[PDB]
Image 1: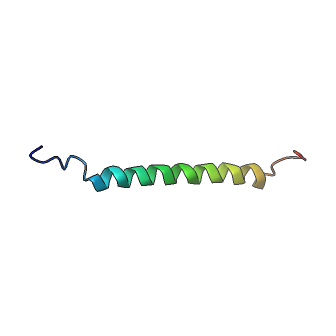
Image 2: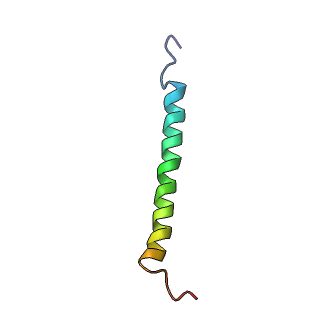
Image 3: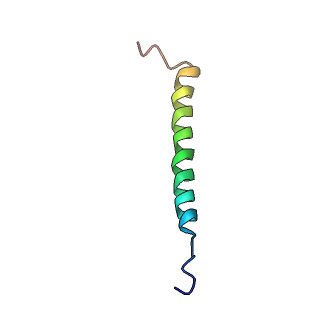
Length: 43
């Protein structure tokens, strides 16, 4: 209120952006892990 800086709107947003991006990397990596370790004869 006197300082609703609390989280610079930038910080919430900055955290949101990082959080989503970090998850995305993990998502891609397993995808690639599936295929690089050699997905499978899924065929």
